[PDB]
Image (spheres, rainbow, N blue to C red):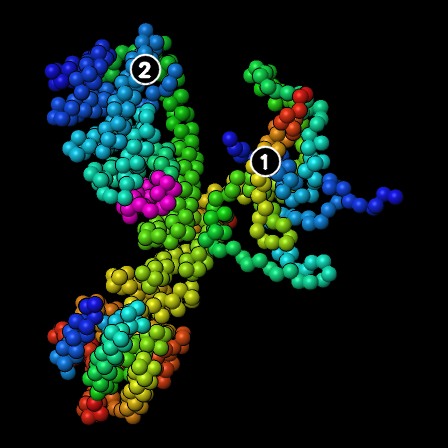
């Protein structure tokens, strides 16, 4: 047979975050996930007044906190947006 | 080394990586195209300047990235108390006249 | 170490007169055998100050900030005595319905 | 010899580069005199405009390069003198302050500003700090473009980050000194006249474009300066150090220039928090923010409840005056309830402060007279009679207390 599995790179996967209401409602088996507490107003003002490097402004449905790309993700975006080979060590 | 996302094209791309809508592995594979293999390493300025002006792939653009860029471009003093009250007032009194 | 000197000065001042300093001493980490003796001395000084100002019509009003501070912070007996004094002062003030011009009634109550 | 060389340099600075080299070679009293002469010569010979890095033009460029090299050597010597650290250090500090005041637009000004910031970043009050602060304030006031002010703000931000937002209170006061946030004829040939007319037209067009460019540049610089200041203030507030008062004062001063959404969000940060003094400052800042023209119950409740722990006087009087100055927001039988606690707490503190507090309600346009006696129900936590003080206030250590009570009655 074929085990009817899922590959690690399948185009369909859970969690589809969107442009930053809070979707902290439930989970599998119909249990309510605890809503993470809203961040401190001082910290929220700091983030809003100073955008972090690679500030996407996208929030995952599970938590209200924004999702920001890491250094390697900023590196891949730089290569992709500047139209070069997205692999640093691959002889073209 | 850093990078400043100011082009809406990059923001549509940056949104896709973060929002996980488009898989990262698929994005890497989609980056091996006719334009990525047209390398720009060491070319003279008189050549590159026209190449960017002309031979620039036009990637698709999403309204969400447009809003996010406007949010980034929104300065701290873009709309303070005066620029929201008297600037609204001058338009209002103009319409009245 | 210098708390007994402050208590002696407070007692001398109370005798000459006949709260914030006493509250700070009571709320001090030392007060809040020597510590027990200092606490007892502070309670006695507070009682003497309360008794001296008990004649005033505004005795419950003046002792209200001290009562709130004491409640937030022998101590139970002092708080109960202060609450009883405030209740008696409030009852006397309620009974003394005379206008401010007729200050003789307030003085007679005092 | 130094005076003769300085006079020769003043007369002919173009061909007196060796005189500067000789002065540097000749460079405690002699060293101080040489440094003063070098600073005076540099100030007299420095061009008033920025020198663009690379016989009419080539020789001038060579002379500018030689002058820049001499200034760099002088700056390097000054940095070593400052790092060595008393009279010589004070003289060097004075020379640095003069250079900042005069050659702010010249090259290496960032290095001079960095050296001044490093000297002022010390926890102890080093000599020349007042002069450096005065020079920075003058530069901030005079900088209409704000490019130098933005560079100084970035330098101060780096120093604050290095010091973990733990510096002298006067350092934060430099932010409030930003003026941007606080805002017959000779004969001419026939061909010459055509050139003059064209030059006049070009000058008018350039001036109009420069004014528009200046407006855009000032707005951009102001936004960047505000971003740096707000971030530094927010970081200081997060640290909750001893500079909270300076941060609150800076926040109150620069709150008007921020966005409407930021102003509304600032209330939550203020309400989210010497604890009594910090609460009083937060209440005062909230009142100041609400006092903005063209426009808080938790802050009002905190202010009312903070009176008992207090029992600073000028700040309390200013807050009460601002509350009274509010249009129809007070004197609706609520002020008397608020003033009842103030009268009760007035049994202590200086008589002048108590008299001023009494005069605040005495001069009030409200006709209520029961605030000094039994009054209406005491809501807002209460802790008092719901339903006297002057009688006890008469018996006080200060004889004038009885006279004030009699006058009030």
Circles 2 and 1 on the same chain? no
- Decide which of D366, B94 is in the foreground and name it: D366
Where residue A27 appears, as percent x and y from the top left, is 69, 58
Q: Chain of mark 1?
A: A
Q: Is residue D77 above or below residue C85?
A: above
Q: Residue furthest front?
A: C33
Residue visible at 41% across and 60% down? D273
Report the predominant secondary structure element of the magenta stretch. helix
Instruction: Tell me the element at label 1.
Output: helix
Answer with left or right where residue D47 lies relative to residue D229: left
Q: What residue is pinned by disc 1?
A: A72
The magenta stretch spans residue D165: yes
Residue visible at 41% across and 37% down? D221
Where residue B55 appears, as percent x and y from the top left, is 65, 22
Q: Please say whether residue B66 is visible from this viewpoint.
A: no
Q: Is residue C99 above or below residue D253?
A: below
Residue visible at 65% across and 29% down? A86
Q: Please say whether residue A24 is visible from this viewpoint.
A: yes
Q: Chain of mark 2?
A: D
Q: Is residue D285 above or below residue D223?
A: below
Q: Is residue D249 above or below residue A78?
A: below
In 3D space, how far apart are the residues under numbered discs 2 and 1 (Cα atoms)? 43 Å
Answer with left or right where residue B11 lies relative to residue D110: right
Where residue C60 appears, as percent x and y from the top left, is 29, 83
Q: Which mark is residue D65?
A: 2
Q: Which residues are magenta?
A: D159-179
* Quadrant housing residue D371: bottom left
* Quadrant housing residue D295: bottom left
- Decide which of B33, D290 is in the foreground and name it: B33
Residue visible at 35% across and 52% down? D241
């Amino acid at each position: 047979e074929i085990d009817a599995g899922y590959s690690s790179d399948s185009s369909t996967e859970d969690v589809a975050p969107g442009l930053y209401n809070l979707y902290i409602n439930y989970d599998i088996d119909g249990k309510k996930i605890t809503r993470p507490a809203t961040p401190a107003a001082l910290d929220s003002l700091i983030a809003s007044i100073d955008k972090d490097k690679g500030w996407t402004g996208i929030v995952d449905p599970m938590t209200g906190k924004p999702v920001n790309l890491t250094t390697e993700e900023l590196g891949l975006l730089k290569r992709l947006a500047q139209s070069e080979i997205p692999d640093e060590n691959f002889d073209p | 080394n850093n990078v400043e996302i100011v082009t809406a094209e990059a923001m549509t791309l940056a949104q896709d990586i973060a929002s996980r809508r488009k898989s990262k592995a698929d994005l890497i594979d989609e980056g091996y195209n006719r334009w990525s293999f047209q390398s720009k390493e060491g070319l003279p300025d008189w050549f590159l300047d026209e190449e960017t002006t002309v031979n620039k792939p036009n990637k698709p653009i999403t309204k969400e990235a447009v809003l996010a860029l406007r949010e980034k471009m929104k300065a701290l003093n873009a709309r303070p108390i005066k620029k929201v009250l008297e600037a609204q007032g001058r338009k209002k009194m103009r319409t009245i006249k | 170490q210098l708390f007994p000197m402050r208590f002696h000065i407070i007692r001398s001042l109370i005798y000459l007169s006949r709260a914030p300093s006493l509250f700070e001493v009571l709320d001090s980490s030392y007060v809040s055998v020597y510590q027990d003796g200092l606490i007892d001395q502070l309670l006695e000084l507070l009682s003497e100050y309360y008794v001296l100002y008990a004649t005033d019509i505004s005795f419950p009003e003046l002792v209200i900030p001290a009562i709130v501070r004491s409640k937030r912070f022998g101590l139970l007996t002092l708080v109960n005595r202060l609450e009883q004094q405030s209740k008696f002062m409030t009852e006397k003030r309620n009974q003394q319905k005379f206008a401010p011009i007729d200050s003789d009634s307030v003085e007679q109550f005092a | 010899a130094l005076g003769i060389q300085a006079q020769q340099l003043l007369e002919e600075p173009v061909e007196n580069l060796h005189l500067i080299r000789n002065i540097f070679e000749k460079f405690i009293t002699i060293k101080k005199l040489s440094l003063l002469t070098l600073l005076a010569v540099f100030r007299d010979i420095i061009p008033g405009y920025k020198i663009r890095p690379l016989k009419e033009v080539a020789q001038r460029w060579e002379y500018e390069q030689t002058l820049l090299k001499h200034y760099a050597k002088f700056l390097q010597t000054l940095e070593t003198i400052l790092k060595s650290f008393l009279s010589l250090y004070q003289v060097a500090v004075r020379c640095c302050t003069k250079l900042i005041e005069q050659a702010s637009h010249f090259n290496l000004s960032e290095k001079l500003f960095a050296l001044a910031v490093r000297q002022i970043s010390h926890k102890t009050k080093r000599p020349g700090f007042d002069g450096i602060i005065n020079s920075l304030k003058n530069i901030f006031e005079e900088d209409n473009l704000g490019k130098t002010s933005l560079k100084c703000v970035t330098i101060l931000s780096r120093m604050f980050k290095q010091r973990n937002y733990d510096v002298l209170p006067d350092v934060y006061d430099l932010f409030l000194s930003v003026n941007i946030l606080n805002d017959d004829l000779p004969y001419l040939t026939k061909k010459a006249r055509k050139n003059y007319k064209e030059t006049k037209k070009i000058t008018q067009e350039m001036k109009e474009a420069d004014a528009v460019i200046t407006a855009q540049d000032k707005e951009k610089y102001q936004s960047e300066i505000l971003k740096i200041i707000f971030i530094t203030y927010f970081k200081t507030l997060q640290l909750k150090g001893k500079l909270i008062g300076n941060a609150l004062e800076g926040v109150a001063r620069l709150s008007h220039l921020l966005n409407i959404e930021f102003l509304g969000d600032l209330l939550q940060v203020l309400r989210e928090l010497q604890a009594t003094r910090e609460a009083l400052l937060t209440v005062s800042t909230a009142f100041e923010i609400a006092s903005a023209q063209g426009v808080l119950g938790l802050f009002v409740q905190r202010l009312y409840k903070i009176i008992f722990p207090f029992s600073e006087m000028e700040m309390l009087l200013k807050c009460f005056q601002v509350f009274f100055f509010k249009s129809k927001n007070i004197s609706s039988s609520r002020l008397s309830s608020f003033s009842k606690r103030l009268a009760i707490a007035s049994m202590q503190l200086p008589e002048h402060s108590a008299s001023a507090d009494l005069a605040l309600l005495k001069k009030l346009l409200s006709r209520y007279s029961k605030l000094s006696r039994l009054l209406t129900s005491e809501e807002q936590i209460g802790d008092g009679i719901y339903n006297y003080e002057p009688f006890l206030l008469k018996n006080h250590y200060s004889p004038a207390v009885s006279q004030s009570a009699k006058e009030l009655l």
